[PDB]
């Protein structure tokens, strides 16, 4: 289990392979675990408040930050947040092969785009919710949304059976 010093970030982009566990906290923190050859080949950089996780040339990553605006899952793996999350506007994009699991989100605006292969399973209380599943997989939404704009152009399904409108 390696700890890395990282600059303040409010967005996360992962282009390599790995499981991310996110915790909302006033303290920024980055911890990585796995085989030494994969941990040493995992590059982390913060540019203009965006945390970039990629290859230098499967790890488990624990991240904490007070705010989260964008999650761009360009690579392969999972993005998990099981603890309560209170945000303003947050967007989740699965372009690669990914899985987004958010157990307890409160926000103004939620944006979800499953462009690649995978799934998004989110429990949310929000004012506006936007979801699109153009790829191959499924989006499962539960909780409540004041307004919801949902489309499913791809292969799979969008499940909103337990999502309250209003």
Image (cartoon, rainbow, N blue to C red):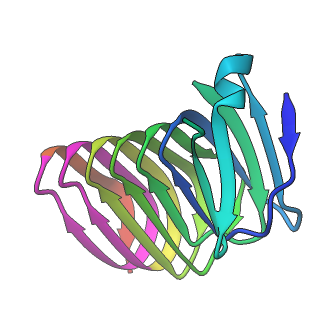
Q: Residue at x 64, y 76 (%)?
A: 48
Q: Is 114 rendered above or below residue 11?
A: above
71 sits to left or right of 39: left
Q: Is 64 rendered above or below residue 60?
A: below
Question: Looking at the image, how many numbered discs can be counted on the residues?
Answer: 0
Give the x, y percent position of residue 124: 51, 63
Q: Quadrant of the C terminus?
A: bottom left
Give the x, y percent position of residue 125: 53, 70
Identify the residue at the far front of this view: 57
Q: Is 20 rendered above or below residue 133?
A: above
Between 8 and 87, the one nearer to me in the picture? 8
Q: Which residues are magenta?
A: 128-154
Q: Is residue 43 magenta?
A: no
Residue 89 shows up from this direction: yes
Q: Is 20 rendered above or below residue 111?
A: above
34 sits to left or right of 90: right
165 sits to left or right of 61: left
Give the x, y percent position of residue 106: 60, 70
């Amino acid at each position: 289990s390696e700890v890395r010093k990282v600059d303040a970030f409010s967005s996360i982009e992962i282009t390599s392979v790995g499981t991310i566990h996110f915790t909302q906290s006033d303290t920024y923190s980055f911890r990585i675990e796995g085989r030494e050859k994969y941990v040493k080949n995992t590059e982390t950089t913060v540019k203009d408040g965006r945390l970039l996780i990629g290859f230098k040339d499967g790890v488990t990553i624990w991240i904490s930050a007070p705010d989260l605006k964008e999650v761009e899952f360009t690579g392969v793996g999972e993005f998990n947040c099981e603890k309560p999350l209170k945000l303003d506007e947050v967007s989740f994009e699965v372009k690669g092969v990914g899985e987004v699991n958010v157990a307890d989100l409160t926000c103004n605006v939620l944006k979800v785009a499953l462009r690649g292969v995978g799934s998004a399973d989110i429990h949310v209380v929000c004012d506006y919710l936007s979801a699109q599943m153009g790829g191959v997989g499924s989006v499962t939404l539960s909780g409540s949304a004041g307004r919801a704009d949902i489309s499913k152009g791809g292969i799979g399904g969008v499940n909103t059976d337990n999502l309250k409108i209003g």
